[PDB]
Image (cartoon, rainbow, N blue to C red):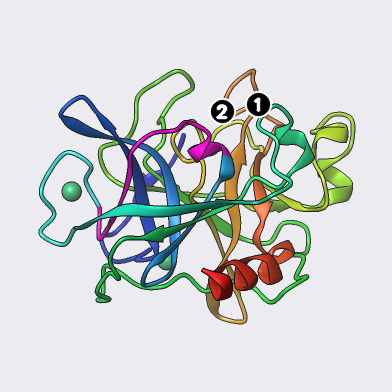
Amino acid sequence: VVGGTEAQRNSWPSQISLQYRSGSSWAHTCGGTLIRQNWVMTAAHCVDRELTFRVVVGEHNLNQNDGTEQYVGVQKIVVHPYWNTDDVAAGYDIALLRLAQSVTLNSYVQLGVLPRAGTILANNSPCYITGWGLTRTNGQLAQTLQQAYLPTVDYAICSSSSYWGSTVKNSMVCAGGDGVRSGCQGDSGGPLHCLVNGQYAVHGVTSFVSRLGCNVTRKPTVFTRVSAYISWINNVIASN
Ligand SMILES: [Cl-]
Ligand code: NA
């Protein structure tokens, strides 16, 4: 997250860190949202590589013992069947991870609430992106979870020529684009949390930023629209 602030330890308990084994250590690569005690929702492009992955729930600082983490291996991966890694603009950037163990819930570990199917936020709806992604374009990952306030940009505006043009689809949510704050590499797969009727719900799964930079004016962060996949999610969990 570029232009973010440090999140309080218990603000976003459904946020997880998706990590891969690197030598004798684990490296954060993407965020995710805990949606069942043994299921995580993340971006399909985060699991394109055939690596060993683990999820960390109750994570706040990637580099220091928080006293609250639960480390759980990824046992099964279900990528959306229409995902194509060389066509992120087509959409379908979503995948579900079944965990090897069911995590224990508490104030640092909770399930993310998803929006009702088909829900589309009005332009400029207030939302927060959260993640440990780069804090600057071509920078480094954050040590502590960051949050940034990114209002939605509706399809009509987001798909206009000065914004994302034909690249954005109605199956995505755009947010931000002010040139100061945005998601960045390493935030992919994580949540876009938006307050609706007094409750936050996870409306987006971070998918991509501009090749020209993370925080680029009129290039809002683009997320997979969670509300377009409610039936898909329910169907995968019911058959797995
Ligand atoms: Cl949360
Ligand atoms: Na930690």
Judge from the rendering whether residue 217 lies leftward or rightward of residue 165; answer left or right. left
Q: Is residue 119 above or below residue 41?
A: below
Q: Quadrant of residue 194?
A: bottom right
Q: Position of residue 22 (x, y in %)?
A: 26, 27
Report the quarter where the N terminus lies: top left
Q: Is residue 61 visible?
A: yes
Q: Which residue is mark 2?
A: 214
Q: Is residue 116 above or below residue 54?
A: below
Q: Position of residue 167 (x, y in %)?
A: 81, 34
Q: Nearer the viewer, residue 171 or 162?
A: 171
Label 2: state its secondary structure: loop
Q: Is residue 175 visible?
A: no
What's the residue at 39%, 65% (across, down)?
A: 14
Mark 1 vs ligand 1: CB below 8 Å:
no
Q: Are marks 2 and 1 in contact (CB under 8 Å)?
A: yes
Label 1: state its secondary structure: loop
Q: Which residue is mark 1?
A: 210
